[PDB]
Image: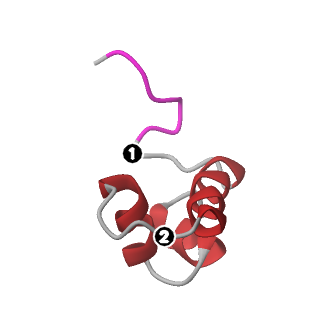
Amino acid sequence: MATIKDVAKRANVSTTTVSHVINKTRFVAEETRNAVWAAIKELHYSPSAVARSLKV
């Protein structure tokens, strides 16, 4: 599915890894960082918006 759930697994393991990157707290290696951003786009992650993500 195009959710953070699937993305987290494809990226590394759990949503924790994704949170670390986005929140920019536990600075992971560029490998994990890139994997997260890549997975997010690859799975076409839909933040409660199948259309897209812009405006308000």
Image color mode: secondary structure
User: Closer to the observer: label 1 or label 2?
Assistant: 2
Q: Nearer the viewer, residue 15 or 2?
A: 15
> Relative to 50, is 49 on the left or the right?
left
Q: Which residues are magenta?
A: 49-55
Q: Could you say whether the residue bearing mark 2 is in a helix, strand or loop?
A: loop
Residue 33 in magenta stretch? no
**Of residues 45 and 15, which is closer to you in this image?**
15
In the rendering, at what x and y percent does residue 27 appear? Answer: 41, 66
Query: Where is residue 24, by image quadrant?
Result: bottom left
Going from N to C along the chain, the mark reached first, 1 or 2, is 2
Which element carries disc 1, helix, strand or loop? loop
- Identify which residue is drawn at 54% across, 84% down: 13
> Majority secondary structure of the magenta segment?
loop
> Can you give x and y, in whole percent of width and height, for residue 26 in the image?
34, 70
Residue 45: give x, y in percent of width and height: 55, 50
In-image side of 32 versus 47 (left or right): right
Q: Residue at x 66, y 66 (%)?
A: 31
Q: Is residue 1 above or below residue 47?
A: below
* Callouts 1 and 2 close, C-beta under 8 Å: no
User: Label 1 is placed on what type of residue?
Assistant: Ser
Local crowd size for mark 2, using a 10 Å CA cut-off: few (<14), some (14–19), many (≥20): few
Q: Nearer the viewer, residue 28 or 12?
A: 28
Q: Which residue is mark 2?
A: 28
**To which quarter of the image does residue 43 belong?**
bottom right
Q: Magenta span has 53?
A: yes
Residue located at (53% from left, 30% from top): 51
